[PDB]
Length: 119
Ligand SMILES: CC(=O)Nc1ccc(C(=O)Nn2cnnc2)cc1
Image (cartoon, rainbow, N blue to C red; front, side, top):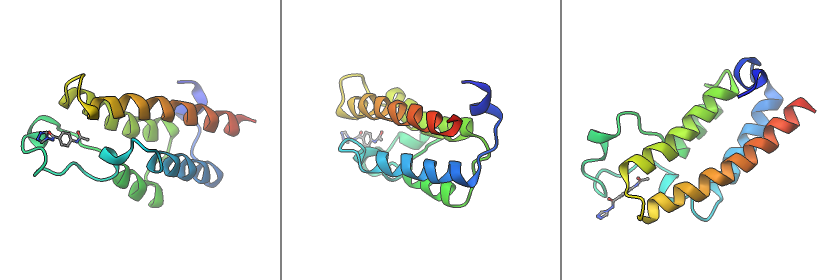
C-alpha cells in the first residue's frame, strides 16, 4: 500500500466513495454468504475456529458511524471477510469460490476509488 492509503485521513468525500464501494459489493450476485454474520446453526464450530469474524453488515454499521480513520483500516476489515472464508472452508466448496470472485471484484473497485482520491 502507498503512503496515501496508509496515512491520509479519510475525508467526507472519501466516505461517499467508501459507501459506493460497499453498496457495489452488497449488490454482487456472489455476496450472499457475506451479507450478515455467519449463522452458528449453519456452522456449529465456526466461532470456535474463527477468532475475528467479519461481515458486510458490520462494515456498513462502521461506515455509517465513521469508525475508519485511514483507508488501510477499511481494507483490513474487507480482507478479513475473505481470509476467514478461505481458512474455514475447503478449496472445493461454493463458499471458497464466492470469496475468490468477490475479492477480485473488490480489488477492481478499490483501484477505482484510489484513482479518484488522487486526481
Ligand atoms: C461465510 C461462511 O463461511 N459461511 C458458511 C460456511 C459454511 C457453512 C456450512 O458448513 N454449511 N453446512 C452445513 N452442513 N454442511 C454444510 C455455513 C456457512
